[PDB]
RNA sequence: CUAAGAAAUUCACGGCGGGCUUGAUGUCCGCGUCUACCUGGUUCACUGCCGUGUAGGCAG
């Protein structure tokens, strides 16, 4: 569970240097808020209106979308809610989402 | 015997999508040139007001949240400001042939089910179920929130043989109750028409028109779609409403759920009121299943006892089982 | 400050705008009520705000004469807020007062409008318009520039008056019908 | 093995043609003993003129590329070589082989000296990277400016400075400069743990790590094993094979003032970790510790787990 | 008992999008044929709306249904929690009617809080209010919205009758459909301020208009019972009762005058707060919303 | 479309808490439909053989 | 003070010629998406603005 958040942060870092300006791309369905959840470049292109949209608006929806994708990575059945092992999985999902959100809070901040 | 591992029934009483239009009361006679209610768009902006986790975060973060509110755009639908009266119109086919499956593995289970339902039919007609359906047409259940707080509601039901109105019914949908099912002459006529339709002994096509005064320009309530995220939040990632060729509309399953609020016969009470007819007969707004499967009252237990082993329940639970067969579904394993 | 009067004022909420629109609407209502009847020497008095902060101010202290700015609280179309805050009548403010340049004062508060207008319709060519509208030709002076929340210009700019900077011993005098002390250092309450 | 008073992030270093052999039994990333010797060389040539003490090193290895090839039907790999100049008669040279690789590593240097208060942090950082830009790191040249050497400034950071929130905050602000990185640590105790697990047949430690960098296909009554991490074999120091000699005794030594013993290197285990999974950064650093009366010369990351 | 995981309340006092039409004063009885106010272009590229140059008096018209059944939710997990909440709201109603909330709602209708910027700088405002059963005037009430202050809720008998009507509507004892007409002198050719879409102005079928939720915000400005200050003014009724312009969360949960804290203390553990705090809680239920977890 | 749980539950996990919590998460779906217009009452179906 | 320190893989080349992928088919039955919202700085101490020139009548 920690390896998924670690690999996701490593993938965001490895993508967040090659593209100079992380512009809004046609077809960025996960790039609606992932236009700042991805590489946010505060250049002349990504101006103060981009530096203020991603400045004040945080990537919690990227974090909440990532937490939903982590919940939907494995399936959902009577084992995730009818046992303490599913309770352990839910507590680990909440802990990993809180850890990734505490990481992303210092990203734009 | 065993149950069929693949049963399937088809929906009887299938309605259309209801379309909303708008006009002035005392023009209900000329209520056919009336312009449609058009799903518009507006921009809202509101604070954070939900039950935030108490002492999750510091109150300076609460003060900072109000500095940065969200702003979203929603679909609304209002009457035109000259008009005070909504008009909701749909059509209904009462098909009939109710106990016959449309997919069935077992050849003896089909015969036993059809003998069971034929025993029900010649034992007692569909007059109870059709009387309750004629209630849910005469009172405007299908005006879901559009009835709530409305001053006057009138339902007009027409029978349609050819391109021609055969018999017309008119009602006062507020004087006819929402909870009790009483006796009336015109509703017994409509009940025996719907009962002849369900029994397979005639053709029934109804035109159901409901006239609810609300006031000069108020909000009407179509049914609501869910949002695919090709277009951004600037562009309704908040609220889309349902429509047709530029007219505000209600889904057909919404109206059909308003029609099969039959079930007074569930072990809690009838003082709560009738509910919809579901297997494990549930309510979405209450968030619970009435008619639990550990009690012996859901559709599957009653059906398997009455078909496989001839344990005929009480008459009202037979009305429940036949009403689930009129609803239609994907039954079986 | 050269303002011989000190108009009484008191803050309060406003529904038609925030506190910035509250201060802009208050200065506009004062300059359209008191500066709608008579008088010329109705200068500027709003030095309670910080100089380097670059704000318009919120201290309820009008800076005009008695008759030249007293009719702001008795405006013939200036109702709707006469009881929502602590109001009053005319009075006299201290001699040491900041000449808050929220008025029709004349300075380099706009290189585009006033500067480009002197380049275009001031006996000059387009080179004068290019030399008139730099970044140092459009900026407010050291005075509390009230935001002109009225039908002043095509856009909604402020009441910019590039006068002498934020001080205490200003020299005020004859403003115009729009109530401009942006070059006349006037006192306040 | 002193605890560090600071950390120094040599931020981004392209290495030209390093040594990708590392041992007689490995071939990948170079030995961490090269990194320990590099930081000790920086301790020699500028680390005393600033009155500091550079001990730890944190390996990062952003981008890797080795000069190898797989020879067309064979499953293993071979190395790409160089032409050496000709012989004395100009015939040809006898070929020895050397693997060569291109690293992009980042170094985290622990500092212990009393000169941390006498000098500004930027002058320390500038002089360290300006000296290290003229050195070599695994037998490989440390490359200057390229197309995207924009994070050219070195940074210095005292780990003791501030509150616990301040320390952990400035830590997680450092980890934003290790972005595709993968830190290399020592995992000796896991080697002994798996040896104590599978020590039924043979408790030889060579068989243990010789059956860990692998896929272990177990059969029907296929259940291949699960990888706990990116466990890779490393060399982990030297063990003696000779009694130590006086500085004049061994013929053809590098000098005549240091004692020389013939040794054998000493294989180990460690595994690559993202800079988020580590708790702090002072636990990540490599140190050299030797027991000289015996022949145990080794390096590890002490106080990791 | 705990609280319901899903609570939802549907709103009472639901207004319509008010339509602005201009016209001259002393056309004040024949106001049904006044021409509307159009949103147009000026220059930048903005949208503004102004009166015609021979028209001084703005006219704002909207209707309002006062529904009733305020305590009853419309989505609810626990039926025991619903029973306790309905007994709690019935305890409120049998202790005292809605007449205090009705007077404060009728004060927000009697002034022109729904004329947001359009009232600031107006030399006469008249609010005519009709009760409508059929297409008729059952009883009319015309006012003077500058004498009836925006700040200090005074005493008046016509407001008492109009609050009797609104209290009968909030209880469930009658059908209340109020039509609100607000005349306001701004001057000839002056600027009106309709509400602003995501910069364009909000419009209907070729006329300028105010959003419905903004007038619904203008009606529920009641909350004179703060933890902060009883000297500034009334604000709207929100959970975590907040002003966006001021930026301050008044009624913070580090005090105990919060909506959720009051509601949980008075429903679950029967800790009934002060009477004005009960007015606040019932006003947040007349507001409606999605409460619970 | 928004439906509920009406399928034949496997009688090893049919608990009141389990069923109620299954109803707490209603399956949202999207469907393709085909109706007639609100003024047409006839379907024309045409093919060549 | 680093399995330390050193290093030229080179030249040249024709991938061509041919080819039938076919025959057959039922995607079906059923469904409540609700609940609530101020885009209010002067979208400029300024665009048209006596002097573009801290001076001014300035749709203030």
Image (cartoon, coloured by chain):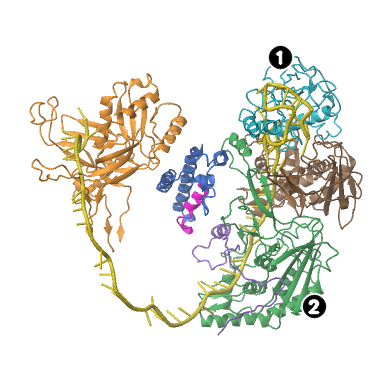
Chain colours: A blue, B green, C cyan, D orange, E brown, F purple, G yellow
- Tag 2 residue: B167
Q: The disc numbered 1 marks a residue on which chain?
A: C
- Name the spot of residue A101 as percent of width and height, x first: 49, 42
Q: CB atoms at circles 1 and 2 under 8 Å apart?
A: no
Disc marking residue C169: 1
Foreground residue among C56 and E223: C56
Query: What range is drawn magenta here?
Result: A62-79
- In the picture, measured across the screen, residue B270 lies left or right of residue B54, that is right
Figure quadrant of residue E284: top right
Residue closer to the observer: D217 or D84: D84
Q: Residue at x 75, y 73 (%)?
A: B207
Side (left or right) of D183 relative to C116: left
Is B201 magenta? The answer is no
- Asked if D111 appears above or below E158 in the picture, the reply is above
Quick one: D210 or C59, which is closer to the camera?
C59
Q: Quadrant of residue C26?
A: top right
Q: Quadrant of residue D187?
A: top left
Whether residue E182 sits left or right of residue C188 in the image: it is: right
Q: Is residue C166 above or below residue E233?
A: above
**Majority secondary structure of the magenta segment?**
helix
Q: Residue furthest bottom?
A: F49
Q: How far across and down, in percent of the image, does residue E172 sit?
A: 80, 53
Q: Nearer the viewer, mark 1 or mark 2?
A: 1
Q: Is residue D23 visible?
A: yes
Give the x, y percent position of residue F31: 58, 66
Element under label 1?
loop
- Dot 2 falls on a residue whose secondary structure is strand
């Amino acid at each position: 569970v920690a390896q998924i958040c670690d690999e996701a942060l490593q993938y965001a870092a490895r993508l967040r240097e090659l593209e100079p300006g992380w512009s809004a791309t046609p077809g960025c369905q996960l790039h609606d808020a992932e236009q700042l959840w991805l590489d946010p470049l505060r250049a002349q292109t990504d101006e103060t209106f981009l530096q203020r949209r991603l400045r004040g608006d945080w990537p919690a929806e990227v974090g909440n979308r990532f937490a939903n994708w982590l919940n939907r990575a494995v399936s959902s059945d009577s084992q995730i809610l009818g046992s303490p092992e599913a309770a352990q999985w839910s507590q680990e999902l909440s802990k990993e989402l809180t850890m990734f959100k505490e990481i992303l809070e210092d990203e734009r901040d | 015997l065993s149950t069929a591992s693949v049963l399937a029934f088809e929906r009887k009483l299938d309605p259309s999508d209801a379309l909303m239009s708008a006009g002035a009361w005392a023009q209900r006679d000329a209520s056919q040139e009336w312009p449609a209610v058009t799903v518009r768009e507006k921009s809202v902006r509101g604070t954070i007001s939900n039950r935030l986790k108490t002492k999750d975060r510091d109150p300076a973060k609460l003060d900072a949240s109000i500095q940065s509110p969200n702003l979203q755009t929603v679909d609304v639908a209002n009457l035109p400001s000259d008009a005070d009266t909504l008009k909701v119109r749909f059509t209904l086919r009462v098909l009939g042939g109710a106990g016959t499956p449309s997919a069935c593995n077992d050849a003896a289970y089909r015969d036993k089910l059809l003998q069971t339902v034929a025993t029900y039919v010649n034992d007692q007609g569909f007059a109870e179920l059709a009387r309750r359906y004629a209630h849910n047409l005469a009172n405007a259940r299908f005006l879901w929130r559009n009835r709530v707080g409305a001053e006057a509601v009138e339902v007009r039901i027409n029978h349609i043989r050819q391109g021609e109105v055969a018999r017309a019914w008119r009602f006062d949908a507020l004087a006819i109750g929402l909870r009790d099912f009483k006796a009336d002459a015109e509703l017994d006529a409509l009940a025996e028409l719907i009962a002849s339709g369900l029994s397979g002994s005639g053709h029934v096509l109804l035109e159901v028109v409901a006239f609810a005064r609300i006031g000069d320009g108020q909000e009407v309530f179509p049914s609501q779609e869910l949002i695919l995220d090709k277009g951004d939040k600037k562009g309704q990632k908040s609220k889309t409403l349902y429509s047709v060729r530029d007219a505000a509309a209600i889904h057909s399953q919404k109206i059909g759920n308003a029609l099969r609020t039959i079930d007074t016969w569930y072990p809690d009470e009838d003082g709560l009121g009738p509910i919809a007819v579901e297997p494990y007969g549930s309510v979405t707004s209450q968030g619970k299943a009435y008619r639990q499967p550990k009690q012996k009252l859901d559709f599957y237990t009653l059906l398997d006892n009455w078909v496989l082993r001839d344990e005929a329940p009480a008459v009202e639970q037979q009305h429940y089982v036949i009403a689930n067969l009129i609803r239609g579904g994907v039954f079986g394993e | 400050m050269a303002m011989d009067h000190y108009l009484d004022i008191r803050l309060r909420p406003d529904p038609e705008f925030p506190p910035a629109q509250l201060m802009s609407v208050l200065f506009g209502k004062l300059h359209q009520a008191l500066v709608a009847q008579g008088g010329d020497r109705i200068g500027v008095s709003f030095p309670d705000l910080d100089e380097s902060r670059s704000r318009l101010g919120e201290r309820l202290r009008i800076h005009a004469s008695a008759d030249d700015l007293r009719a702001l609280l008795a405006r013939p179309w200036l109702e709707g807020l006469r009881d929502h805050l602590q109001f009053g009548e005319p009075a006299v403010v201290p001699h040491p007062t900041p000449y808050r340049q929220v008025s029709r004062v004349q300075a380099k508060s706009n290189p585009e409008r006033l500067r480009r207008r002197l380049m275009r319709r001031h006996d000059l060519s387009e080179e004068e318009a290019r030399k008139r509208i730099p970044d140092t030709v459009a900026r407010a002076l050291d005075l509390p520039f009230v935001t002109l929340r009225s039908q002043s210009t095509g856009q909604h700019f402020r009441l910019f008056i590039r006068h002498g900077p934020l001080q205490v011993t200003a020299e005020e005098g004859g403003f115009t019908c729009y109530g401009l002390s942006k070059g006349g250092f006037v006192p306040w309450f | 093995v002193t605890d560090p008073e600071a950390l120094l992030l040599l931020p981004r270093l392209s290495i030209q043609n390093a040594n990708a052999i590392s041992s007689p039994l490995t071939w990948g990333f170079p030995s961490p003993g090269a990194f320990t010797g590099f930081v000790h060389a920086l301790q020699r040539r500028v680390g005393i003129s600033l009155d500091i003490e550079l001990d730890g090193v944190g390996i990062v290895c952003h981008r890797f590329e080795a000069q190898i090839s797989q020879p067309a039907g064979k499953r293993t790999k071979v190395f790409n070589l160089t032409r050496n100049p000709l012989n004395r008669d100009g015939s040809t040279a006898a070929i020895v082989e050397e693997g060569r690789a291109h690293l992009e590593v980042s170094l985290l240097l622990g500092v212990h000296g009393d000169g941390l208060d006498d000098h500004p942090a930027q002058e320390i950082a500038r002089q360290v990277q300006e000296q290290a830009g003229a050195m070599r790191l695994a037998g490989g040249s440390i490359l200057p400016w390229c197309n995207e050497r924009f994070p050219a400034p070195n940074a210095e950071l005292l780990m003791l400075g501030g509150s616990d929130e301040q320390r952990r905050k400035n830590q997680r602000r450092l980890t934003r400069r290790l972005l595709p990185g993968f830190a290399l640590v020592s995992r000796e105790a896991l080697l002994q743990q798996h040896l104590e697990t599978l020590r039924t047949t043979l408790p030889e430690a060579t068989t243990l790590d010789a059956l860990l960098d692998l896929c272990r296909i177990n059969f029907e009554p296929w259940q291949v094993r699960d990888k706990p991490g990116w466990l890779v074999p490393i060399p982990a120091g030297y063990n003696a094979l000779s009694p130590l000699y006086l500085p004049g005794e061994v013929r053809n030594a590098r000098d005549r003032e240091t004692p020389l013993r013939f040794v054998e290197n000493l294989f180990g285990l460690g595994e690559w970790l993202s800079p988020h999974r580590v708790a702090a950064l002072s636990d990540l650093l490599w140190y050299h510790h030797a027991e000289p009366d015996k022949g145990l010369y080794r390096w590890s990351t002490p106080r990791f787990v």
